[PDB]
Length: 124
Image (cartoon, rainbow, N blue to C red; front, side):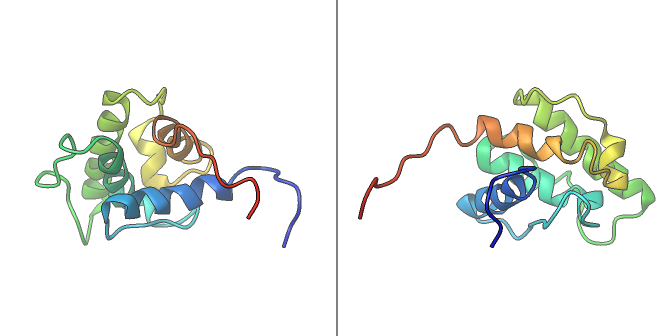
C-alpha cells in the first residue's frame, strides 16, 4: 500500500474499467502502455457507456486488426471522443503506437464528462 496520491495515473485506468462495466463491455485495459489500446477496441466501448446510441460497432472492427485495421479502429474512436466534446485533440496515430504521452489524457478527458461527482457516508 502506497500513501499519498501522486501521479494520478492508475486512477484513470481504474475508472476506464468501471465505466466499461457500467454498461457491460467485454473490453478493458490495464495501462496507457498496454498493447491493447492499439486495437482501439477498449476506447470505443468506453465512449458508448457515456454517450450510447452514437457508437456503431457495425463499422468498428474486431479480432485480428492488421496495421491498416488498427489505425481504422482508432480513427473512429477519435472522431467520436471529439464528437461528444471531450476537450481532446489527440491524433489517431498515438493510439496505434499506444504512446503514454497522449494515450494518458485520451482516457482522462473522457472521465471528465462521465463522473460528475461522488459522495459517500461520512461515518459508518
